[PDB]
Each structure stands twice: as C-alpha cells, then as structure tokens.
Image 1 (cartoon, rainbow, N blue to C red):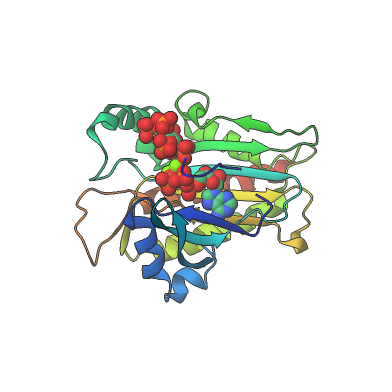
Image 2 (image 1 turned 120 degrees about the vertical axis):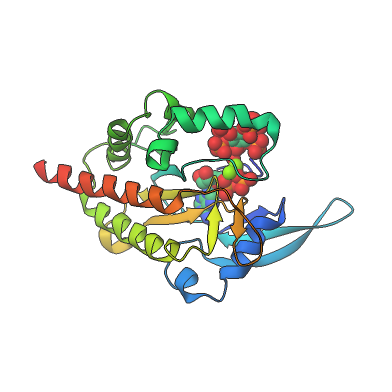
Length: 246
Ligand SMILES: O=P(O)(O)O[C@H]1[C@H](OP(=O)(O)O)[C@@H](OP(=O)(O)O)[C@H](OP(=O)(O)O)[C@@H](OP(=O)(O)O)[C@H]1OP(=O)(O)O
Ligand SMILES: Nc1ncnc2c1ncn2[C@@H]1O[C@H](COP(=O)(O)OP(=O)(O)OP(=O)(O)O)[C@@H](O)[C@H]1O
Ligand SMILES: [Mg+2]
Ligand SMILES: [Mg+2]
C-alpha cells in the first residue's frame, strides 16, 4: 500500500516507512547466502530522495517482472501468525481471525492474491481475501497454486522444479534462526511467453517491514516461517506428482 502496486521498469523504489525492512536488507547485504543465492530481490541500496521538507529513505531493488509480456503473479504470505510484537491493538482481532480462518495457523502459509494474464487482458485478478473462503484448506491452496501454473492453454509443469529449488535455498538459510519475519511473502512470478531458457520466472522472499534481527533485539513470539516454507515445498512436490498424470 506504500506505492501503486502495478511492472515493466527496471526497479522498485520502495519508501522506508520504518527501520525494519531497510535494516534487514543492510544486514544481509554482505552475506553471500542471502545475496548470491537469488532468494530475495537484488538490493541496489538505500537512497534518500527529496520528499516533503527534506528527504525520505527508499530501498532500491529489482523489479522482478521487468520486461514481462504476460505476467502471472501469486503472493503467498508465510508464517503461522501475521501479527508481531509491534502490531497495533486495533488490528489484532482481525489478524487473529484471518490467521485462524485461513491456512496460516495450520500450514504456516496462505494464499494472498493472484493475477493471471491469459490473452484477454486486462488480466484475471484473484483477491487476497479468498484465503478465508475459497482457499482456506491445503487442498484448495494446492488447487490455486496449480491455477497459477495454468497459463490459459496448459499447465507449465516444467517451471515447478525451479520453484522448489528456490524454496530449498530459502529453507537452508532460514534454518539458521537469525531473523524472524512476519507478514512477509514468497512471490511467484513468470511471463507466460517465456521459455525455460529465457528465465522469465522468479521466486523470491519479499516484504520485510516486520523483520526482527535476533542478534540485535528480542522477539519472543514465533513466526513459524520455516514450518510454512516446508509446507509450501510439500505442496509444490505434490503438484509435481499430480502434473505427471497429464
Ligand atoms: O487495516 P489493516 O488490517 O492493516 O488492513 C490492510 C491494509 O488495508 P487498509 O489500509 O485498507 O485497511 C493495507 O494497506 P496499508 O494500510 O498497509 O497501506 C493492505 O496492504 P496492501 O495495500 O499492501 O495490500 C492489506 O493487505 P495485505 O497486507 O494482506 O496485502 C490489509 O490487510 P488485509 O489484507 O489483512 O486486510
Ligand atoms: N521487487 C519486486 N518486484 C516486483 N513486484 C514486487 C516486488 N516487491 C513487491 N512486489 C509486488 O508489490 C506488492 C507490494 O509490495 P510490498 O508488500 O513489499 O510493499 P507495500 O505493500 O507497499 O508495503 P509494506 O511493506 O508495508 O507491506 C507485492 O504484493 C508484490 O505483488
Ligand atoms: Mg503492504
Ligand atoms: Mg505487507
């Protein structure tokens, strides 16, 4: 909500509305395990740009859908809760209900919006709010992720291994227990006009406004992040299995 949410320019220049996202990117900046692994957007740096009477800090990162012709986008919110120690009390009844009535508390992952461009664009939009009704079980989440891989003509089964490979790299780094992340997402994207060789597909962790750096501060509550990644990987592996019957 801090910028118009739509992706054929090179960058995203995201405003720093608090310290957390910028501190996270700065903290992982020299760690090849975060920056050489391709699991978060390429981070260009924190920059000041004129704003108001002075300057506002922004994060400059890559636009993951740069030059995508027919973008497919799926945002999956990770964790067994989406509130954190700083969440405003006026938001908490809703946060608790949405967490318990989606797949968040059970799986540590939930559907959080999709866009499919099947030739008749403007594209088909799938509301993030579907998580508490249409996409409120493991089975239905699996179905909606399959729909992500449906380009309007066929299931892009050949892309699924990439996505699992990305989740593995995420799992490997998130076993280290150095950060807790709340309301962060794994963003799946591809251009349906892509071939495997074009590499116009991507799977990245995003949205670090509620990240806690455990070597610098206390965060007692659990995020269930690794649990969610493992469940999501399990769903993708089931999908690989299911796509062989095609
Ligand atoms: O009031 P909250 O419970 O935090 O609800 C918000 C919020 O919507 P409203 O401002 O309309 O209530 C968001 O926008 P901001 O206020 O943070 O700008 C939005 O974030 P996005 O605009 O980035 O989508 C978001 O949705 P989400 O974080 O799920 O994408 C959503 O939370 P809910 O989706 O749970 O209503
Ligand atoms: N690097 C990126 N490349 C392409 N799309 C992105 C990128 N980062 C985010 N997006 C898209 O923009 C949406 C919003 O991004 P994000 O949630 O990071 O920011 P925000 O909603 O403005 O602020 P907050 O961090 O407070 O939620 C995402 O759901 C995703 O669809
Ligand atoms: Mg937001
Ligand atoms: Mg957010």
